[PDB]
Image 1: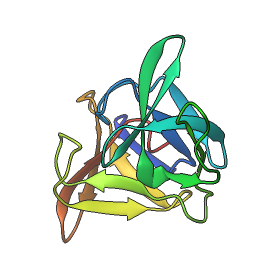
Image 2: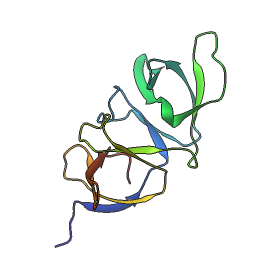
Image 3: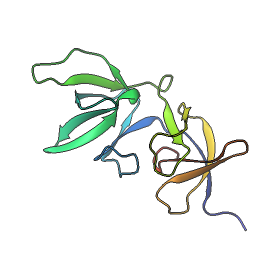
Image 4: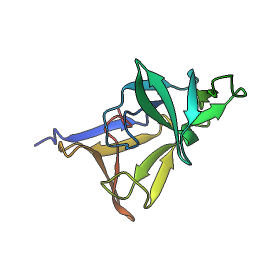
Length: 137
């Protein structure tokens, strides 16, 4: 009777390098806390960088600015440490805006993976909340 789709884990200590400005996309890489890399300023929320002549995006609130821009305009950023990193959990399956619960890494959570493309977290007072499949392990 054991629920094979029910999992018990914790919040990851990495930030996704997404191919699009969408958390529901498959990340190209997962950047551990404290990882340093160069990005450009794309818009209000997202950074951008080029790998193999391909554009990947990174959420700004996951990074720390540690240096001034270079001659190319690249910002040397660093993924926030586990003390400061905050991982989102949306109230909608679209994983965009709405209500968001922000979790620090290593915080224990129980979710459900029913192949919907996202994780499902039940809250006794708030109902169903969702996050990305890579955010909880």
